[PDB]
Length: 146
Length: 146
Length: 141
Length: 141
Ligand code: HEM
Ligand code: HEM
Ligand code: HEM
Ligand code: HEM
Image (cartoon, rainbow over all chains, first blue to last red; front, side, top):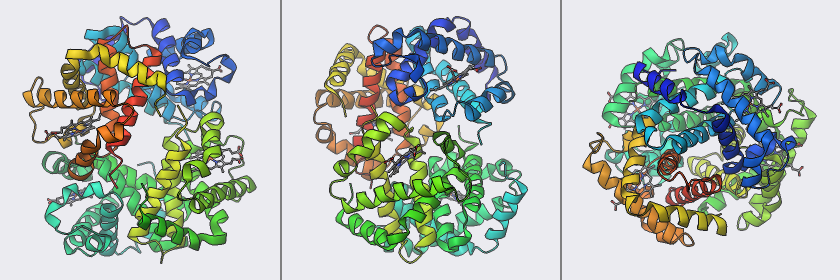
């Protein structure tokens, strides 16, 4: 986005240390748990009755990996999140009917998961750069809504 | 701001009918009355203790006219709000220390004021155009914050 | 909290809405769909065309609920319990959308009650819709 | 509404913070200032540089107030009456900002209490900060 060279590098370097598999399953699960209303799109996933049930759900786990996968790829197009997510933006609007506010919630959950994982390494300035990315991605995903 | 030409014509047509002096005073007064926390910036304005004290305060009326004056100019540069509002953005940030959320509250209040004044003439689609405009101005005013 | 003053203001302004509540409810929805398109994600099953019977029908429902909250201004949490449960457990509308509808409700009233829509009434009506929104979102988690 | 599990979760997590609450208070502010620069508009009289004594001192104050709130989790409105007054009538911070500090506090806790920051605890702390926010902005109008 309006990422600084130094900001671009910090994002880039932390991400290189991320296990998308684990972080994706954790981010989505935490979302379903912290903000229970988000479960409205995943009725077909099964048992989301408890934190334990959400966190253990493999459908949740596999969806999280798909989402973070797409997010991951977007980090390669930080200069055109808009064009990178145009088709996904249309899909989310036109087929999935997902309120873009959900993109924002996930973003913040993602930031908590990174802090959780990297502790010390996730410094205030590194958080600042990720907040910009997360906001940039949410905006890009919401861009084609009409 | 992404305003279809037909949105731009609609904005411009109505604005032709507005008495900026009067609307400015009404919009600013209502802001201070509906969101009293916004009064934090005007302790030198005197008595803002009741709705009548606010609405009739000669200082609120004069300031309102100044604010809407700047806004009307913004309406002739819908193309370049960021540029138009850059020095004002800097001032609000660096000198006045005004949280940008204030700009969004004023925009919403202004929309109610236009609805109040134009009645049926402020159609659903005219409101949609003005919502885009007010958001663009708030955004332009917050662009230089740091 | 709503003060005695707020309560008087709301009963008075809503009093004037009278028989038009339904039509105003529908208009508020249309304004919301046009100004905040993201709210449409909740009505994928509706015909959102101008003059949709579904929108008309839905507008009445919303308006009836507000009318009911005014009638029970001293016991809103109980008067709206059912609606609070529905929104929390079935509809699961994200909280931010309540502020969007409230805003379009205020625009609609402003457009129709010029004489009653005073600064004081505007303030009371805003606080009221905020309170209704809070009740409807109270059982979310 | 904090459930009994929530209150427990909160008391547990906060229990672990202990002597570091002031440092965490300070770290959460620093994260807020950097991530959401608009929040700095409320502290024009502070030195917002890294490790400023004003920020440190302020972090302590906030942490202390949180502690007191956990301690009176059952009686928040009352334990925080003075702070609700201060914020509503003097400080007049726009309500949107409370969500930003709350988020920065979660991030700070996450970063320092890895074993304790489970999904259920995360849920509880969020609800807790939301409740604290509600109390602090309840007398605004
Ligand atoms: C970082 C933001 C997000 C990204 C990059 C993203 C990306 C994706 C991708 C790549 C798919 C695959 C489907 C396909 O290509 O047909 C998908 C599907 C989906 N996403 Fe999103 N997503 C995001 C956020 C969300 C959020 C926050 C929600 C709701 C809470 C959501 C709900 C869904 C649903 C319901 C599906 C369909 C899955 C299925 O068919 O089982 N997404 N998303
Ligand atoms: C449409 C959005 C706005 C525009 C176009 C605008 C424009 C202006 C202008 C032209 C001035 C005078 C500049 C100068 O003194 O050199 C001003 C001053 C000021 N504005 Fe803004 N303004 C807007 C919104 C707001 C809001 C919402 C607030 C607070 C709630 C605010 C707070 C102030 C204050 C406190 C001053 C200085 C008043 C004084 O002289 O003591 N403004 N604004
Ligand atoms: C203060 C504001 C609100 C009030 C008074 C209200 C009231 C109602 C009522 C009375 C119903 C009908 C339930 C029944 O069948 O008995 C309903 C349904 C519904 N509401 Fe809410 N609501 C509010 C806010 C919202 C918002 C902001 C949204 C989304 C933007 C929303 C989305 C829905 C949906 C999707 C339905 C189901 C419609 C259908 O399938 O027929 N509501 N609401
Ligand atoms: C989690 C919610 C919050 C809590 C518990 C809290 C608590 C406090 C406390 C304990 C004080 C010091 C009171 C005294 O001096 O006796 C204070 C002051 C203050 N707070 Fe709040 N606060 C919160 C949220 C916020 C937010 C979000 C902002 C603005 C972004 C803010 C802005 C201020 C300011 C500007 C002061 C005065 C600082 C000074 O001049 O020393 N507060 N707060």
